[PDB]
Amino acid sequence: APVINIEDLTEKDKLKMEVDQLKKEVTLERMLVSKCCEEFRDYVEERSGEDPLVKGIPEDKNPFK
Amino acid sequence: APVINIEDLTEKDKLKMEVDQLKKEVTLERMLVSKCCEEFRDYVEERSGEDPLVKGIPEDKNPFK
Amino acid sequence: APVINIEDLTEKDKLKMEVDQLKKEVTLERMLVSKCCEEFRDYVEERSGEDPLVKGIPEDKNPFK
Amino acid sequence: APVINIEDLTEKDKLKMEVDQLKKEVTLERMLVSKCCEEFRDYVEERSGEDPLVKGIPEDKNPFKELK
Amino acid sequence: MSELDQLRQEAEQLKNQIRDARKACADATLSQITNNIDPVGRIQMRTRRTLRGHLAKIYAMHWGTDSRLLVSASQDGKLIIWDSYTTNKVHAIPLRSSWVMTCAYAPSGNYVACGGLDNICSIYNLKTREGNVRVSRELAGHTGYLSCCRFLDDNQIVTSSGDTTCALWDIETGQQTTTFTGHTGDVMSLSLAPDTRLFVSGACDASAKLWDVREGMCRQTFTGHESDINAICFFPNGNAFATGSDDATCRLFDLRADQELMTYSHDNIICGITSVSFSKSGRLLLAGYDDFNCNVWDALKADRAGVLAGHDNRVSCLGVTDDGMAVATGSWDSFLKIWN
Amino acid sequence: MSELDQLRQEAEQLKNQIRDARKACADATLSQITNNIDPVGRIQMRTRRTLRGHLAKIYAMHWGTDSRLLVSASQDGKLIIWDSYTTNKVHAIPLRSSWVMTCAYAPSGNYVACGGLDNICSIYNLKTREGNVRVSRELAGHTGYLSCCRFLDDNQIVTSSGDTTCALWDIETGQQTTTFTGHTGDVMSLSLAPDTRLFVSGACDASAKLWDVREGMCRQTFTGHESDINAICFFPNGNAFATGSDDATCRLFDLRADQELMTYSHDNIICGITSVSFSKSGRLLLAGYDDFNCNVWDALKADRAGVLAGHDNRVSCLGVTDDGMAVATGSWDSFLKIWN
Amino acid sequence: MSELDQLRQEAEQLKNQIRDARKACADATLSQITNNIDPVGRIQMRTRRTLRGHLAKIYAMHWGTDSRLLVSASQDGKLIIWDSYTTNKVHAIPLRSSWVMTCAYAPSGNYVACGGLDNICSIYNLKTREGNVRVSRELAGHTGYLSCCRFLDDNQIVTSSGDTTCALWDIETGQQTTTFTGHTGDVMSLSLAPDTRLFVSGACDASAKLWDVREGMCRQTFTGHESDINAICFFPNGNAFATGSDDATCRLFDLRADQELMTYSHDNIICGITSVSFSKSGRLLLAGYDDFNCNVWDALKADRAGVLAGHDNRVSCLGVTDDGMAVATGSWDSFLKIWN
Amino acid sequence: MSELDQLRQEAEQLKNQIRDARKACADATLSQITNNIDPVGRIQMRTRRTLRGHLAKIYAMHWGTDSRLLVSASQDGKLIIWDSYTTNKVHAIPLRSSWVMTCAYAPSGNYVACGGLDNICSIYNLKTREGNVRVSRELAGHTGYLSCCRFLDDNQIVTSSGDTTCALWDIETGQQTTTFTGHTGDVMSLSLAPDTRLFVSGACDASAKLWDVREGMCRQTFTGHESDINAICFFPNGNAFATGSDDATCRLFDLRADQELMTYSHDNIICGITSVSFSKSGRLLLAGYDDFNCNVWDALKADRAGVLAGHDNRVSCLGVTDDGMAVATGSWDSFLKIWN
């Protein structure tokens, strides 16, 4: 949208916007949380092996040493 | 005040009053929902069989028609 | 098609046949129970009405009256 | 069977003995699993402290160390 | 500044503690505990009466002690006392205001009350003053609409209001004996416990509160709903109560449990609930819906056992006779309907 | 060497994999998915007929496809063909053995079959016989009691035996065309798929098996029961079946899922199940119990919608007519009753 | 309009539908999907650096893209740009208002920003201007405190404010390019998507909202939290984000799922979360609490993998370096600490 | 027919009754109760020693109460006793039989025992007889292989056998003092309680039974595993015990609960469990697997904390020292490995 001032909005204004935002979200194509969890798991799994905080940082490669 | 009361307190007074109510509720001795459910079941069960709306009413005995 | 006399089988014969079956079953393409449940529901629903034992039978049409 | 009866029963005497065992078992006073889980959790909690295999042990104190 | 932070953070921690304490006690739902219970099946009630008389949307109704006489109120500013049996209008009280939101019948049968956007609860003597039914009292003191009222006796009545409060009134003196404050939204309805020692209120803050009538204080606040509680009804034994809400669900709360025992809803029912009532035994929980229908739930199985379909408009109110022989449904279509 | 070691281990691992593969698909029970479906409404069937004759316990019964005639087996060594409509005993066949365990009515109405501790499935010619009804064939081969039998047509019949096997017989030659081996315990019941291309068997090994009639092999084996399966019946669409067990539960198993969809039991029903059968639509799952009653389950909701109570002894068999108009219960009390 | 506002009821009805739609997709949780996953091994990070310099409560900190330089903000009116490797503060910018609440580091490293109760987001040039590091711009427009700010680039910054809105700014012209309104409560934090096409805000209304930068609209609003969302952080891949709240829990939300994947909490943790951040892989979700502690959660197992305990007062903020090499924690104890 | 089916009826009903009784008590899992407990992280044990000597598959092992001298046997009929600390044969006892399924160590360390397909339990005095160390007692009685044996004391030993019975012996008379009958399947192992006054056995009938040593009877039977229980191990406090099984799952059982508290298994672990043992605190549950590997489970959080990999063949046995200092693993690869 543009740039709007809140002071310029009345009760009716807001309620109407709320309903108009509600009308758009209701149409969302929601993915199954299982699928999302799988994709999430896979992503983290393909990278944690090289995560300094997880695997540990060697006392020679640590910049804060 | 005297009997009635008009809630015209300050924000600090409302919150204060709020934690005061919460502090009361937090000390509540709660019954397990399982025991509550069983009691609710035993109460209704010894009465539902003769509940006019559950068992229906014989034509002749209906105060309405 | 085949006919077998269980007396012609030894403990070893039975085992081999057992794991042969298991090997066949492991490759079974299993459907989601939710999906099987929905299809089961739909099938039953398309017929619940026309079920003398569910819907009931008019006395004049009840052959066992 | 028991010591006073090494083995001497029929294919029906056993059914009687099985139900007798079941009659006794059915009346076992059973504790709630959560209750057992808390006592278990607790026992292990005031114990995991000195568990060698959990907290490890220094080589110098490790019974299966080197030679010195 | 002052210690405003420590107060809001304290409120939160306490809230967190209450949620955790409740969580630990939530070991099952009614539906599971009722495994061995047979459903009542499919309930099919028929309209036995269509009380026609109002020319405008009905907003409230209340059966009287005799389960025959019942009072109704509509936007035309009229309070009609009907004799359900005969379908005779025993009274047609003109009202100083048209926007009536509630009505109650005194247990004695000697008075009726009502109110709404006028912010006034008017008592009307019916019996003792045979002739023209005149307003004997106008309880004023609330700074918002009267959403609900219920008589404890002839000289005492409790009221709920959009002003966020409820009050116990001494009728004769017209004074607010006690003021119940706590809700953070318009209180939409109230129900008095059978023993009258306590009563409950449902509000727009999506919570229900249990109050001790005598001490004037809040004992417990029940949550779970995610919308305004338009209706609230005490259960026969005084240990539980149901709620109707705009989140399209009815709920059963237990005082001792301090939380709900069960929620009644289907993913295909999205409209708000206006009213709630228990059948005599409490086995059935009947609720009025914005979709013009009344869904009767098997309270123990959570089955939607029946539907009372007949109104061409929003079912705004409903009630079950004391003898539990029938149920009345009020609707915006101006009609009242008795069913059984 | 290993040989047997590796084989019995190989077997265990495969069972684990299947279990794991099944859990991976277990994601809902039938009652959950049927949340929005209305409950059936208390099923209250009344006894229409009381077929009296067998002066001894009835062990089995099968309805003829005309929904009028049916055959019952009794320990008094008599196979009786009844006209349920008139209550008249159309035939009272004396048997060579009083221990009949099963009986079957051929789809054609021309023959009936039966067998028991005699390990024989005897076929009786009803029609063609110009006069008295005589045995045409005695099928011998099983080395254990005949637990159940069902014709495919006049020349074909499938049997189940306490000897752990099932068999397809060519009655003309009196020979077994196919043997079905796999169970590790007495087979107690069998049920043919609506198209007769498959059949399912339940046995004392606590498992049910799906067999391909033509191929002569086990397609799948379903588990879940904690005790022997005494009853089994195919669901109308051919993709599912119900089982009755000594564990006091009935189960609905789906072929595509390869596991159960729902269990039906009350923790206060501890007695065994002798018989199981669906209503025409499959909405109701009727089951006979050792407690003298038949419970009618709502297949979709998993609730008990009704009870058939009239036998003064164990209900041993039951069946619903092809027209879905009646249900017959056979009992150790000597009687058969028709309900609707 | 009139009595029942079609809008107010339409809002409820739509909220109900969305709830039903989400519940339908909520089959499992993340921790159930990760059972096979082995635990990460107890994280025992240690302080490698203790940045000393502040004399009062630190409220914000933000790593620079070089994973070495960082800026912090304190209520004493000071904005310090430190060097985490040498503990040398490169700058010590005194501020007009002492009540700072936020600070950001421009991706380029050329500027930093901050704001708070003065409702202004002041931009500072500390590069191309050798000498007295002065405020380049003072973004005025918010009628409420600045709760958080993040640069998209040198000329663009997004702010969130206690006035209920968020806004995109053109620093050159000092004007608001886009305003993001929708929240009904004070926005507390925001997080830019990896590609800066979207950003997410968490507010006191207990909801988080995803906004599209270019189109300047709100695409989704996540719910679940029981109170204020004080912190928020985009996940590395941009398909999920975590939040910290006064309800004592951190949550992981997935944009496609339109709801949460997992909740991280222990019933013995009742205080509030002030900040939240992910490790480079996403395996860890680090959170700062009001109890002076920082918990490192195993994002997949929902286990607490570790606990950074090193502050004598509330850990007000924390951030993980872009290179995943270290994590810094700011606190009301005046100190900042780097761990790994 | 027959009284037999009546006893059959009674048994089934009692069985279901017990199932329902336990169902009422299974109110939570151990993992759900340990949610607040932090995981141990990742256990990483390394092999300290590798006891070489056996020229064939090791089938068992047992530490001496001194936590240093351990006995072990193998398919090459060699009951070897070693000094774990130094890695050397303190004894190398050749047995007349190579098929040794078990071996025990006297709590006094004065004797040992072993047996297998020979259906005998041979005791060996390793001290009171200088130089020539041989069988000072052979216990004959069992009509099936000796699967496991455990020393009560110098003159008392209890054994389990494929003959489907466990037995208490008096070494002096060689007489089976007490017999324990109840299992309907070949017993595979036993484990004494801390007091030794009671013991528990795991049999092929997929059930573990608790027996009173003095009374020689069955206290209770435990179910759960859907396959044979290869191993069993009493918990340090004597109120619970673990079991290893072919269904690839380890389970925790509680004597007072009369049912399991937890199951340990991952859907990708399908090989059977051979051995099972607790760490000193009981925090860790180690199990030996057919996949040549041993997994260490966090008993509290049900997480797989680690895995002792190192055996070229199936891990057949494993024991944890009395001082909890180390664990030893026996494998079909003929080698033993100490881990600390």
Image: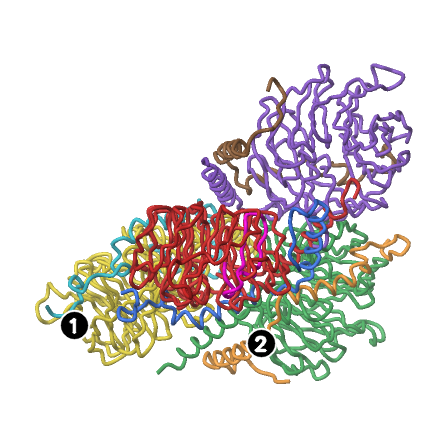
Chain colours: A blue, B brown, C orange, D cyan, E purple, F green, G red, H yellow
- Write the residue at 29% across / 59% down: D54
Q: Nearer the viewer, residue G12 or B53?
A: G12
Q: Is residue G160 magenta?
A: yes
Chain letter for mark 2: C
> Which image quarter is the N terminus of chain C in?
bottom right
Q: Nearer the viewer, residue F194 or E152?
A: E152
Q: Is residue H252 visible?
A: no
Q: CA distance from mark 2 to mark 1?
A: 51 Å
Q: Secondary structure at mark 2?
A: loop
Rendered image: mark on residue H87: 1
Task: Tell me where residue E280 appears, x and y as whole percent.
Answer: 72, 34
Which residues are the magenta region? G150-171
Task: Tell me where residue F15 appears, x and y as whole percent.
Answer: 49, 72
Q: Is residue H85 visible?
A: yes
As drawn, is F184 to the left or to the right of D49?
right
Q: Residues within 10 Å of mark 2 (few under 14, many from 20)?
A: some
Residue type (three-letter) at the residue carrying disc 1: Thr
Q: Secondary structure at mark 1?
A: loop
Task: Tell me where residue G93 appears, x and y as whole percent.
Answer: 39, 54
Rendered image: mark on residue G94: none
Task: Tell me where residue G337 appears, x and y as whole percent.
Answer: 33, 56
Residue closest to the far left: H130
| Residue where numbered disc 2 is placed | C28
